Length: 289
Ligand SMILES: Cc1cc2nc[nH]c2cc1C
Ligand SMILES: [Mg+2]
Ligand SMILES: [Zn+2]
Image 1 (cartoon, rainbow, N blue to C red):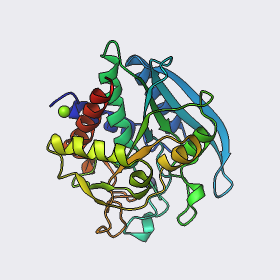
Image 2: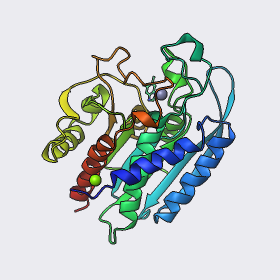
Image 3: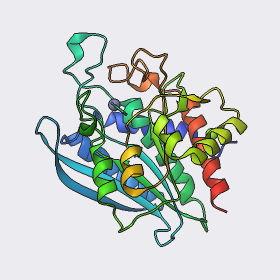
Image 4: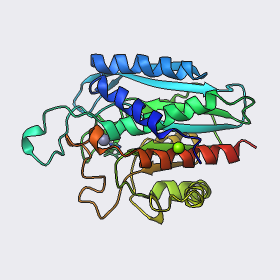
């Protein structure tokens, strides 16, 4: 199956990275956001932006910019796809205490999910007579928190889930992609995903298995990860899963590149992007019925 161009997704990641770090409040962030909006529109999506001024953990006032792209916005049966598009300002997990004040590319952490969903949006824009509405949401200000302070992360998704772009917004299911591009990635059952959306997690992991991606989508418990999907679950009641590279066997749970200078384009593996994208596209295809 090649409904999902791995080369194209890779290129989308590289473009994001070549803007420079998409750090909230900086010029590369603004330019990359403009480009994301324009690209989604070029793929036939109706795109709107949700802006707000939000207070970070350190009092910094961030210009949150969520990006919402919709196909068939009038349809009542909807599918939701999510990723965060900001970059963490500092790679304060670098295994070199000197780099805890510098910037990293966020190729996997932010770039990968956005790239996969941009390629999926291209695919969808080529479809005529979609069977369901589809919303692609790029959350801002996901990666600006402090460790141990759970509420300081996922600010864009908190805001959107508490203030959706349409009153009573509902989708049948939600899929969040987070760090879905690194070589050797392992996608285990994230706890909140399986606890609140067991049917969706089963369907997606079995879809991946059927496609030959059981080496990436492992049918075993992973971590309990408070990601952008949890506010959506809690405040909108949408069953959401999180496809995220994480393993308790990793020193940090997340890949060793996470929040280091090594989260750059050299960590990206086209085959991982392809596994995730082919899986998600096949699931969508079998849901628009
Ligand atoms: C702490 C944390 C950091 C992240 N960075 C990208 N996704 C993330 C998810 C969590 C839960
Ligand atoms: Mg493919
Ligand atoms: Zn991060």
